[PDB]
Image (tube, rainbow over all chains, first blue to last red):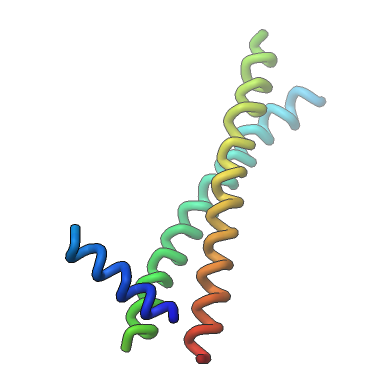
Length: 16
Length: 41
Length: 41
C-alpha cells in the first residue's frame, strides 16, 4: 500500500 | 496592426503563463504535505 | 530585425514554459487522484 511504499522510502532513508 | 497585437501579446501572455504555474506549484506542493500527513495518520 | 528578435523570443521563451507546467499539472492530478483513492481506502 502507498503508506507501505512510504515505509520503504523511510527504510531507504535510514539505510542512506 | 499585426506587429502591435503580436508583440504586446508576447509580453502579456508570457506574464500570464508565469503567474499560474508558480501558484499551481505552491498550492499542490502544500497539498502533498497534507496528503502524507493524513495518509500516515 | 527588431520585430524578428521579439517574435523569435516569443517562439523560444513561451512554449518552453508551457511544456514543464503541463507536466507539473499532470503530476498534480496524478497525486490528487491517488490521494483520493487511497484516502477513501
